Length: 271
Length: 124
Ligand SMILES: COc1cc(Nc2c(C#N)cnc3cc(OCCCN4CCN(C)CC4)c(OC)cc23)c(Cl)cc1Cl
View 1: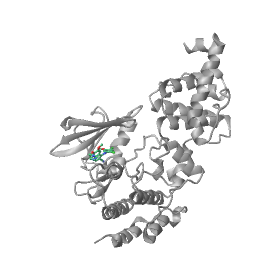
View 2: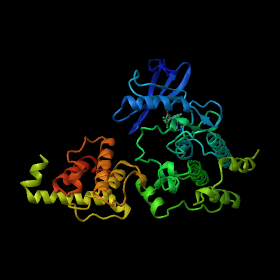
View 3: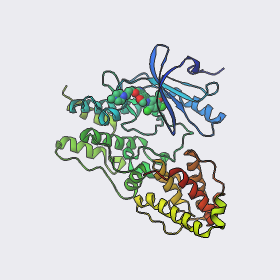
View 4: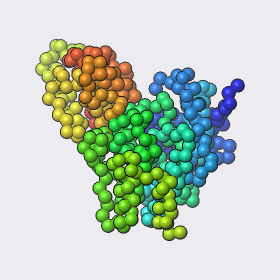
């Protein structure tokens, strides 16, 4: 018999639909006393092979051992569920993107922003110790969630499954130039993640969406082929300027590791 | 249906072609690309791939297709990949074979472009 049955789809209480797009639907719900979010995945040409792969790839995402990583609580196997489905806890503030750019009630201060940066760096350092790496679509402000005590957490629900279309990139502004152009097996994926963190630093400094005026296709082609880069923000400390520049080094090999920037960010805390 | 617009109204065929030319430039000009000729400028598959990302809001990683195809076979692969992107976005499997586009069949080309126009004419 199988090692895991996964979560029983019949035990999910679907409360309210949150959104729908190309990749599927997000719902707020309840399961075994937990407030959850459910992703119902939309997959063209679903097959036994893809279902087998989904079920092999989901257990890796159930990471309960680090405060700055948000696990997949579990997944519904399809069959017998109607559709392949992922479950996480509901994070009350939503994504870092929501908190920074759609924050109608208060503006997070820069002490909180530095704490977000440290949280994300700690979670990424931990994920980078895993062997092999867990494939993700990308680190960006939509794949980081903000929990009830404002802890930032890297969402494992951003997993990239072996069947999902590598040809469509929806947040290229956070992607390293080499990763816009080369297959992942031909890049250092850890160094590519550091570029993404550099763009997150830029986002925390400017409180702007990177390249907001451009479409995703414009961003990817201009960053890859025309050298488009975020402009270094004026009026910031030389220390923050220097950190942003080293994390955004054009040479992937010269970018620091996450475990090197954690102590730098620790020192930038108020405590 | 579309076949009456092609053969037996050649000034409406010219109006459909002028319509499609305006539409594809609305998007491809954002990459500093200009289309003047529907007979050949989509045959190698590159502009169809770039167009799909402009219309459906994604970047296509350059390792996923041949940005500068160097053979008939790579052009066919680009057009096949673009057809997959179209189906990803909801369109039915396109009628022409990918080779029909690479071989500059004007009818095969305008059918594909017209279906993109039917769907995405209001994308900004
Ligand atoms: C389950 O799987 C996945 C889940 C997610 N996404 C979410 C995860 C996760 N992870 C966690 N918690 C989430 C909470 C959400 O809403 C919280 C309320 C936000 N408001 C924003 C505006 N401010 C002013 C008030 C608060 C949310 O809303 C859509 C999505 C969440 C993704 Cl993106 C992908 C997959 Cl595969």
